[PDB]
Amino acid sequence: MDNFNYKNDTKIIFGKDNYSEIGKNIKIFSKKTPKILLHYEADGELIKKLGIYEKVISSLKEFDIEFIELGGVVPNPRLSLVYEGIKICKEENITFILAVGGASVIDSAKAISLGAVDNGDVWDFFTAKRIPQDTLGIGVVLTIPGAGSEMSESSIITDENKKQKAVCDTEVNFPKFAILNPEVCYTIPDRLMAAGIVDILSHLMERYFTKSIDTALSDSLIEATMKIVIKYGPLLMKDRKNYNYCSQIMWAATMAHNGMIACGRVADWASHRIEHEISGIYDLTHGIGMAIIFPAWMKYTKNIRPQIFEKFFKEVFNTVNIDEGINKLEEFFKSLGINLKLSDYGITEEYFSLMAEKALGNSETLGRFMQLNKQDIINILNLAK
Amino acid sequence: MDNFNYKNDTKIIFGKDNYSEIGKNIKIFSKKTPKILLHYEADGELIKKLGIYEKVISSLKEFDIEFIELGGVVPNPRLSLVYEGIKICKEENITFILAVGGASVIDSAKAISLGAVDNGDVWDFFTAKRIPQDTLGIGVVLTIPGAGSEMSESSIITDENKKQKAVCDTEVNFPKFAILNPEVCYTIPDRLMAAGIVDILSHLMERYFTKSIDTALSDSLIEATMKIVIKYGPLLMKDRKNYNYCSQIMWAATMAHNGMIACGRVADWASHRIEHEISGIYDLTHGIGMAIIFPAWMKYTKNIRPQIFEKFFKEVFNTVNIDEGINKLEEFFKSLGINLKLSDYGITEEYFSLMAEKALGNSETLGRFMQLNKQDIINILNLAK
Ligand SMILES: [Co+2]
Ligand SMILES: [Co+2]
């Protein structure tokens, strides 16, 4: 019964053996004669080794696109490099940016696209001083499936001088196009691919367990997507170069980041916030943490709205029994290679209380589906210990 | 394994008690000071009686939007009226068009938005002479759920002087925004509401029965949507002012017209083409016809890819038995009030052969999932007689 609005203008170009689409789509979206800035991480090493670089260069030649290269993106993209990109755009009369890589290259490209067309300081857009109203325009070649910035309206940039991270969220940030080829999955190492599967399922699950009502169709779409991740994830884990398996998983990621299927329901970020503190202290991959934390949060919140738990486990795991369902969900994680206890990762109870306080910050509780105070979070951590 | 591209830039505004969104979204999308053309069918009778008109006028006042009204839209929108709208736009310096109504008002508005910004003849865009490259911009208040032109890139206009219907399909035709309120369903008469439910399910079904492979996730999304139509349609038919029921059905229509869930699969238009000829000769509502024709086509094509039929009936009707499944599908139609035989509608076999020839036109077969020659179509009509 919750009203909602939905919009996503990013053109999705899904599939393989279609590298000509790069220059074709640059022409569709660049203003007059294309002259583009090629943006990537470090000096190309990864994308060059994977053969993506030579493929991009050949699509640019095949359409007579003049291009300048700006490398140097760092996993947490720096305003230092953004500022440099604005200059190169203004001086060299760049018409369009092509981000080749992942969330760091994409977000760097988004902030360069913002400043290139602006007569002030781009950090005003990130620090709530000004509201951007235009962007040069970017396209993305996605190399590693992640949080979906290739179709989001958010850019996250860190100012290393003040050591301050800021976000700019606005419609103009939507990439004009996003090339998605499942083949980029083939080379991701097993552990990180298992983690990324958990991230897709975590992202849907956080929207599913909701106190919103009248979401029958939304429920079914989210169930259908979660079920695919549960069925195909283990198959992909054992057959890494299977195109069908990678397509299903990467289209499920897309469908999860898109939110047409999640429209009209309130998400809960408790497990994400608790996991964040584990990762902030220990070297734990996000997906590995969510596989550990989410079953524990499910057990602790099983009494809030038991019927929505019964529906989830009936629709996704064909069982109305919550405890058997939870065990099935835990077996599914173990089938991707992930150990389920924090102690398995050498994490002891030592910092549970500190983790809970950090997650809580200046509030007494965290969560929406269930409000969690300090001891509640410690109890969830003990369930996962 | 089929590559695909997807894009839809129309902003969806879903829900009720949100008529302020009309003028708010006009301001977001109109170029500088808004001055809009209010477009509708006839002289407003329907939308005025429903109370939609007074609601639009009050949202325009609440945001100081100056507006001119152009009525006169006819169920098959006429270039006559389009041309008139281009003039009013150019003379009166209109910045934005607000279509209040259904597919006819929307398509008329789309062609006026095209010509208002062009220095030539708009019919060049419909007659393959020129490719439109801009539009003034329109927003839609949808009054009757239908084929989804409120989020399509197509406009269908008839030139009554040459009696020629033409279509212009292009990205600029996408409405800037589309207000969708389930409450507009409450007043639709029973027969037409049953037909419209069948149309949503027909639209998904035509994309589902495909010889494309590697569509596991797409299958599941389409199943989930079809299942909702099967479950909630009968409930809505018996509880016409239930907001939850109308929301599920109208969001399923949206999800069906959007095609993110159908991406990467080939549709079959055989039943649509056969039904078209029945409607061309008899006074038969499209949805009523598809409820009669689609089970007959299913029976006739049951041997092409029986496994995809087994999956459809298992996932949507919980049965692996095709014949029992088909009967369940036929019972579902009868539960919306629809009789299933052509003879029930006084349609005899008299024009079966003529209908088949018209549907075939200059080709020997029709269909993709199964190629159907003349006698095949007569056999399908006899199954439905
Ligand atoms: Co998360
Ligand atoms: Co149809």
Image: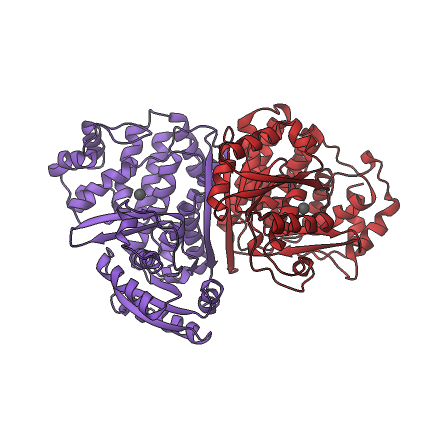
Chain colours: A purple, B red
Q: Nearer the viewer, residue B189 or B150?
A: B150
Image coords of residue A221 (percent x, y):
48, 40
Q: Nearer the viewer, residue A195 or A207?
A: A207
Image coords of residue A125 (percent x, y):
30, 49
Q: Nearer the viewer, residue A252 or B299?
A: A252
Q: The C terminus of chain A appears in which quarter of the rendering?
A: top left
Q: Nearer the viewer, residue B2 or A331?
A: B2
Tell me the residue at 15%/54% (across/down). Answer: A161
Task: Please say whether residue A224 is visible from this viewpoint.
Answer: no
List the single residue furthest toward the front. B91
Q: Is residue A285 above or below residue B247?
A: below
Tell me the residue at 45%/76% (across/down). Answer: A64
In the picture, measured across the screen, residue B193 lies left or right of residue A135, that is right
Q: Is residue B48 above or below residue A146?
A: above
Q: Is residue A381 above or below residue B176?
A: above
List the single residue furthest toward the left. A350
Tell me the residue at 45%/38% (across/down). Answer: A263
